[PDB]
Amino acid sequence: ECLEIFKACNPSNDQCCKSSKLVCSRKTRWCKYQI
C-alpha cells in the first residue's frame, strides 16, 4: 500500500511508489504520470 497514481504525497517523502514512474513535485498534489 503506497501512494501510486492519483495518490497524495507527503512533503516529508514526496517519493512516489516505485510501482510506476509518477511525479508530484510541481504537479498536482496527487502523483501523476509524466507526459
Image (cartoon, rainbow, N blue to C red):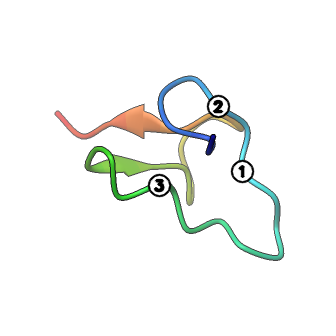
Q: Quadrant of the N terminus?
A: top right
Q: Earlier in the sequence, mark 2 or mark 3?
A: 2
Identify the residue under disc 3: 17
Residue 16, image x and y in percent?
Answer: 51, 56
Picture quadrant where residue 8 is located: top right
Amino acid type shown at disc 2: Lys
Q: Is residue 23 above or below residue 25?
A: above
Residue 9, image x and y in percent?
Answer: 72, 50
Q: CA distance from mark 2 to mark 3?
A: 10 Å
Label annotation for residue 9 = 1
Extreme residue toward the front, this view: 1
Q: Nearer the viewer, residue 29 or 8?
A: 8
Q: Secondary structure at mark 1?
A: loop
Extreme residue toward the left, this view: 35
Q: Quadrant of the C terminus?
A: top left
Whether label 2 touches label 3, CB < 8 Å: yes
Q: CA distance from mark 2 to mark 1?
A: 6 Å
Local crowd at mark 3 within 10 Å, few (<14), some, or many (≥20)? some
Residue 28, image x and y in percent?
Answer: 62, 34
Q: Earlier in the sequence, mark 1 or mark 3?
A: 1
Q: Secondary structure at mark 2?
A: loop
Identify the residue under disc 2: 7
